[PDB]
Image (cartoon, rainbow, N blue to C red):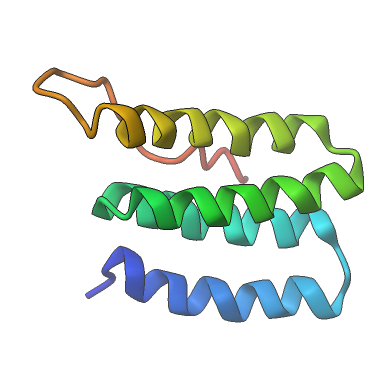
Length: 100
């Protein structure tokens, strides 16, 4: 297995590991990943929460990149809050994992 909401259960543990270390870059990315999992399951409004909280922690770190990155995924979500998906081919893909 490895369902997105079940992956969140691990990412919340990983968030607590980020949080005890107080490393808001990691704390932001943790909630951001959770939000991506929500968004792909159709939990758009739940995705918003996690991208807002992720972004908020990036804003504290002054990492404007991750703040805009969470806001970009927020834009992806807000389109589905206005026109929920819509009958059309949205060119989606996997999360940018260029982590060597």
